[PDB]
Image 1 (tube, rainbow, N blue to C red):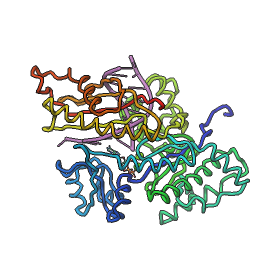
Image 2: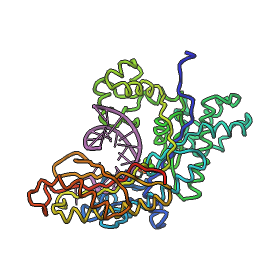
Image 3: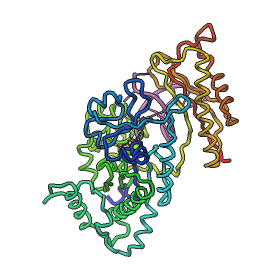
Length: 430
DNA sequence: ATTATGACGCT
DNA sequence: AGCGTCAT
Ligand SMILES: Nc1ncnc2c1ncn2[C@H]1C[C@H](O)[C@@H](COP(=O)(O)OP(=O)(O)OP(=O)(O)O)O1
Ligand SMILES: [Ca+2]
Ligand SMILES: [Mg+2]
């Protein structure tokens, strides 16, 4: 009853860029705007692999993780922009730099957690308290929420999508108690007003559109964001959770899309998030462990406590390349040349990071895959990173992996390497 | 031959 | 520490 926490203490948003690498390429090349188009890396094998797709192209069934030659079968007029290649490998610098543009704008409004190259969480609790005072019990006009959906509405006693959006928004606003400055629903609404402003700023200052979710925690904000993509934002209230979750496949919730989520389904014999409410906390802990069990017990009631971490910069800087099929590295000379290529890109990015962000990496992680293994990594080894020097780093990497060579002859490499990976970690202020 | 990343959990 | 899981 009165002592039952409802997880309505925070206002959290998740902002996610729409079709992000495609928008980056469309800004640069106006010929790609408002077209079925995709971003591809490499080209020789099956036309290259698609890693981002415009919404126009998605209408034809084009997806990421598709080969371009196959995409062209669905969409013959598909336009393609290629990822830059430097030192023999795909280079994602353009997209990392575009990411920084958006992250710096978001940071003006609140402290953010960089969740990926194109999305960030925002804790708006304090900003909302501030704006609520400015408002002075003034109602919130629908005009302040021009791209907002209220999940679950309209309900009860309609043909167009925009028309439906406004119907739901009006029902929501009509029901709002603006008198209470601690009403969670009001707090979410003001949060949504701020996120409209944030999203307008991002589009004005970069040209990029995005979607967003507004709720009381990160998991609901993420879920909300996807409900109305692209170029829209969605408010998921605490009250909307029972209906929303009653038909929500468990795999849709962040962290449940893999083996754990499959185990929840199998062990408990359920399909939807809402069905979890029928188990005790101890029951869930017994199957999924203490931490997961407690997290699931709260999450299926719309409650989660994971903080938005104040972290705008990535914690690691890494460089990776696959050498598939026939291209696997089978000579020592090959291995050394590619370690150098990776190390040179790594040095470049590290030197820029040190200048921009006043920090230095202190640990180098070296990872490889050997032909045969189905795991991402076959072997991961760390060594000290004491100088930002590519030749030193590549020599050090070679030293820590050279023992994996089963070949009796040492100019040859067996089994051949199908992946190299260099990663800089353990930053210290500088 | 679904590539190039990046965070966090386990033991 | 090195490995695994999950994610974009
Ligand atoms: N598996 C991947 N491999 C390589 N790059 C990826 C992968 N997934 C995502 N990316 C890149 C390309 C995407 O444009 C960018 C952001 O990913 P993501 O948010 O999942 O999709 P998106 O921004 O392209 O479309 P959406 O509008 O659905 O968000 O990160
Ligand atoms: Ca996105
Ligand atoms: Mg994203």
